[PDB]
Length: 77
Figure 1 (tube, rainbow, N blue to C red):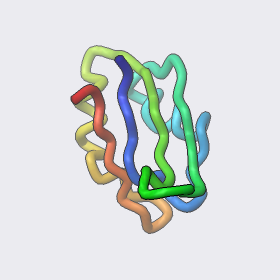
Figure 2: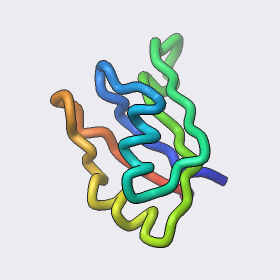
Figure 3: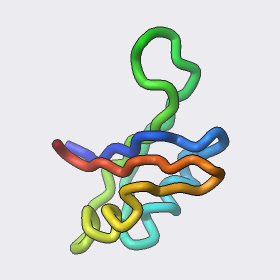
């Protein structure tokens, strides 16, 4: 069970993402994929971080938004 970010900017990265949530949510590992081969995702970043207000401070960025891209931090389900 880990968190998952949706809407990876057109230049987002992994550690940069570990640093995007690790700021208030200790990140243990994350996965970034791109290049949509089929009707599946089209660029996202998983992050199995974990902290007291983790999912909290994370919702504050429910839109993320950075390089003109409002990602969508969504943890668990």
